[PDB]
Image: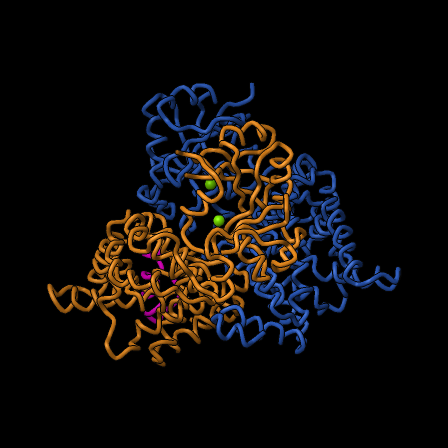
Chain colours: A blue, B orange
């Protein structure tokens, strides 16, 4: 009913707050086609927040669009979606969708959620709401577009996004859009591990991982992704592993909010720590082997388990292992062979994993290794001498 | 004299300590060529220690050493002196010198010091002492070769080497080999700037820099190199700049010896600190403007006149700029920018410069900033937050 809403009444998504990606819409409008702003920004802008990306949408063949920007630095590849560069600014320019494409209204339906589907045009300063969009955005409601049941089945990932946005923005998930999940959760295991990875970092790294974890668990959507971990929760609720994941997420959340670059390998080596430590002690007694070699074995075990669900890059995995290895050495009350560690490119991680280990296990013996490497890592060579 | 010494009369020097340049010498010997092991390690082997390098000399022309090795990996270039590469152990094979190329007695002549001219042949397990070498190396005396006065004028840098070895091994410089230095020192500003740099680092950044600095001051060899510094020495003997330098050395020494790695950008940024700080006081209290901007000129000046003597690469200077910059940033008690700062690459250095600035000045309003940044960088995010 309320399809087109004008500048004065829409929380002024004030023209001037649009990264000059207007210069790209202009070349479109000034070229016969029409161009719009969708999801990402238009959502945030209308809310109030500082948008985190501007995505334009046009009705120009992904072909015509390629022609109109020969002078421009457009990073090709990939169908429908055309890319354009400036500085630390890249502009997504996707053609509508629907023989394939068609109206701006046809496109508004293939999109996932309501709020993420509001259109803005700089030409008339109006925003088109061909979905609950506006109302939902107002009430703080994440609502899936078509028939939940059907869409989820078509692309199970949508279940994850539905919960992610729900935790990222501070709103509740739509009723008819929430029911299906607990059931269909299982449906993710049919997804390339390559992807469940990509989409997993967008959940926990991204800066809202604590809340997003509170949800991914309360919708059994955590199960499919992290079996190796699910397995160890204690109905109790205070397992030291459980605490570790909660904290490491609150902390990784702080970092991302205070702009501090973060480690993806750290995250995993933190979550999978106790389960690793468990499979370590298990193979120890069940095969009377030496601890250092039992643990060294367990690493391979836990990884190809997780790796089975989340395709983790061989890159990140190497580090992880190291972040763990150091958890051994760093305890052995070492001597003049410690400088060697203080130097490891991973000492920082390893340390911060020991910061936590001592924090959650409220173990005084461990918390000593930390108060020690605490001094020894910031000390100066003279004192660092004596210390050893 | 005693020209040749047998393996039964010369310190261990058992062929089994000669890593495997042996395979480079054998290939020559099998070809009707002379293989002598000369220089550093050949000296050390006698003392007992372990050779840090293995170089070899032969009566084979450089274009001959090329044929008999066209197979192996020759990191060629460099007239004379061919480069054989095993990998983490590269061997140098250089041709005898003189009309151009000559014999072993001829080569032993154009060689700087005594102990650095003993030859060894796997062929007959004998060391060749054409120069004083043996005696010198026993008594522990750094004696030059020909006529001190003329060789120093030939290549002034030779004097720097004189102290360098004098410091490294625990030996004394020969009387005749010393007399000229105080007088001839000034001959160093007639030496390319970039070249001094090499030889400057070869002195301090070599893990002997404390003993080598003292010997550079006692022979007035320091002055020609770091004019910008000499200028602020105080008659009283131990100012704050005069402690800062002895410490940065004693420490950069400690590191190198406990096989750590070391930042040169740091070494300098430390020495030249107070001087910069001095050009700040004047540039400020005169032509009076803001301490920040004043301090910004103080940098360009110091580096300019300092880089007039030493040729510090644009690279190194830029990191020096940083370490200094951070000394103010870190100064002002504050936060939220803190993380944005803790993430700075040259932060590790900056901290350690404050480490010293506090030690030397004994000022408890700095040792205070240290006890802070010290704790703010070892504790995890929950505390790192409350500390602001
Ligand atoms: Mg982007
Ligand atoms: Mg060398």
Q: Is residue A142 left or right of residue B105?
A: right
Q: Which residues are magenta?
A: B320-337
Q: Is residue B257 left or right of residue A199?
A: left
Q: Position of residue A193 (x, y in %)?
A: 69, 41
Q: Position of residue A289 (x, y in %)?
A: 85, 61
Q: Does residue B205 appear anywhere in the picture?
A: yes
Is A125 above or below relative to A316?
Answer: above
Is A158 above or below relative to B10?
Answer: above
Q: Position of residue B113 (x, y in %)?
A: 42, 55
Magenta run includes residue B330: yes
Q: Quadrant of the C terminus of chain B?
A: bottom left
> Which residue is most to the left?
B287
Residue under the image location 42 percent in, 28 percent down: A74
Residue under the image location 88 percent in, 62 percent down: A288
> Which residue is most to the front?
B1
Q: Does residue A141 appear anywhere in the picture?
A: no
Mark count: 0
Magenta run includes residue A302: no
Q: Is residue B297 left or right of residue A116?
A: left
Foreground pick, A79 / A95: A79
Residue under the image location 68 percent in, 69 percent down: A332
Foreground pick, B165 / A220: B165
Foreground pick, A95 / A173: A95
Q: Quadrant of residue B178?
A: bottom left
Foreground pick, A324 / A14: A324
Q: Position of residue A336 (x, y in %)?
A: 60, 68
Is B363 above or below relative to A106?
Answer: below
């Amino acid at each position: 009913q309320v399809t087109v809403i004008p500048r004065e009444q829409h929380a002024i998504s004030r023209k001037d707050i649009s990264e000059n990606a207007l210069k790209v819409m202009y070349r479109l409008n000034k070229a016969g086609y029409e161009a719009w702003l969708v999801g990402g920004g238009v959502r945030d802008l209308l809310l109030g927040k500082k948008p985190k990306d501007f995505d334009v949408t046009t009705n120009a063949t992904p072909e015509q669009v390629r022609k109109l920007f020969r002078n421009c630095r457009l990073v090709g590849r990939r169908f429908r979606l055309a890319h354009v560069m400036f500085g630390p600014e890249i502009i997504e320019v996707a053609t509508f969708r629907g023989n394939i494409f068609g109206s701006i209204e046809e496109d508004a339906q293939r999109r996932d959620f309501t709020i993420n589907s509001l259109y803005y045009s700089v030409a008339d300063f109006t925003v088109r709401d061909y979905v609950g969009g506006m109302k939902d955005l107002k009430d703080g409601v994440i609502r899936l577009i078509g028939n939940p049941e059907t869409r989820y089945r078509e692309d199970p990932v949508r279940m994850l996004r539905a919960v992610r946005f729900a935790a990222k923005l501070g709103m509740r998930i739509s009723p008819e859009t929430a029911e299906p999940i607990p059931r269909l959760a299982t449906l993710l295991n049919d997804i390339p591990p390559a992807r469940l990875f990509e989409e997993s970092l967008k959940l926990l790294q991204a800066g809202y991982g604590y809340e997003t974890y509170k949800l991914l668990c309360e919708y059994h959507l955590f199960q499919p992704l992290f079996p190796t971990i699910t397995r160890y929760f204690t109905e109790n609720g205070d397992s030291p592993m459980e605490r570790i994941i909660e904290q490491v997420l609150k902390n990784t959340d702080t970092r991302i909010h205070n702009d501090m670059r973060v480690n993806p390998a750290f995250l995993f080596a933190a979550m999978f720590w106790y389960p690793l430590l468990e499979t370590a002690q298990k193979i120890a007694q069940e095969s009377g082997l030496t601890y250092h070699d039992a643990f060294a074995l367990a690493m391979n075990d836990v990884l190809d388990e997780a790796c089975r669900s989340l395709a983790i890059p061989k890159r990140l995995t190497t580090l992880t292992r190291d972040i763990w290895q150091l958890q051994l050495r760093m305890s052995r009350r070492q001597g003049k062979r410690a400088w060697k560690l203080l130097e490891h490119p991973k000492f920082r991680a390893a340390y911060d994993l020991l910061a936590l280990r001592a924090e959650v296990e409220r173990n005084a013996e461990l918390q000593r290794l930390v108060k020690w490497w605490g001094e020894f890592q910031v000390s100066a060579p003279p004192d660092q001498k004596g210390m050893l």
